[PDB]
Picture 1 (cartoon, rainbow, N blue to C red):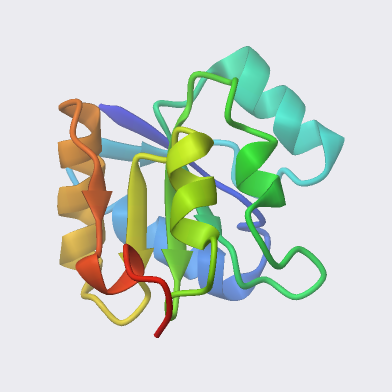
Picture 2: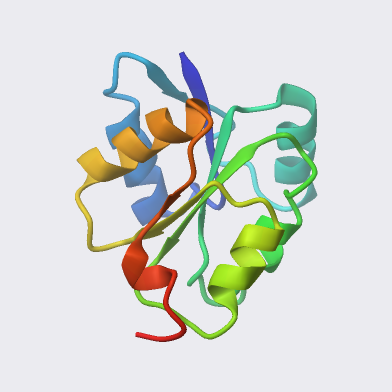
Length: 132
């Protein structure tokens, strides 16, 4: 089973996304509700396979939280609404494996998780662009 950590999943939307991923036979969401240093510690000690981050969270907007997990061994998947300048370059440099549109179905996220676990990088072409 693929172990999945979702940053800030004590929040209802990210918690709901994790509940949906838990319905997959080959996936398990781990460390639910862990935040702050407690989260960074979970990722380092429990070593989840995949880390999902919403980069548009207010008071945590940007690539910094994802860049903070770049050396944890966790395969990062970022969720965003549209392209922002310099984001694609920062994601590639931080070793991000997935860079997806929030508008895509949750089936695309599950498939991206599997692809990322098979050594692939899944970037929405709409986001590899300089702007929206």
